[PDB]
Image (tube, rainbow over all chains, first blue to last red; front, side, top):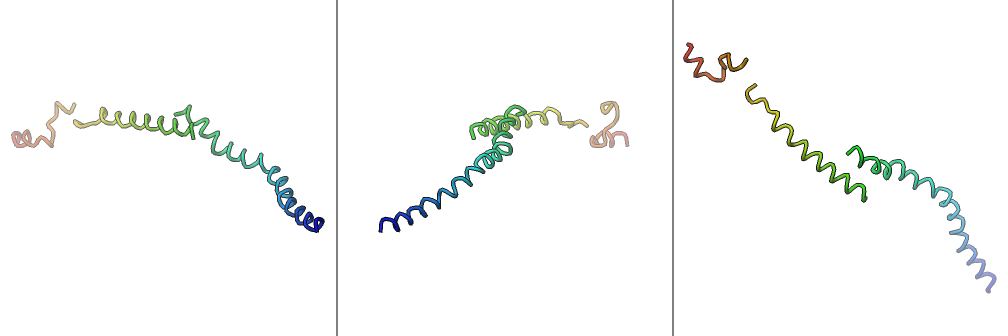
Length: 49
Length: 48
């Protein structure tokens, strides 16, 4: 019973484990998309103002 | 957001300095003094 419940536990672990690597592969990407298009434009925009 | 606040303040400063320039550069009188103005129709009636 512990083995089958731990198989369910392994599924409940891997459902987040598989997603974590994928979202950390793209974790630089979306933050840099916010950087080069939203935050850094406001970083410049103070000085020409 | 912190930079955007100063962006808003500087834009407010820029627009309140924009709004002062057009008041000092109004061509109300549009040598005009030598000639008889057609708007000054009193002088036109005088000449007529």
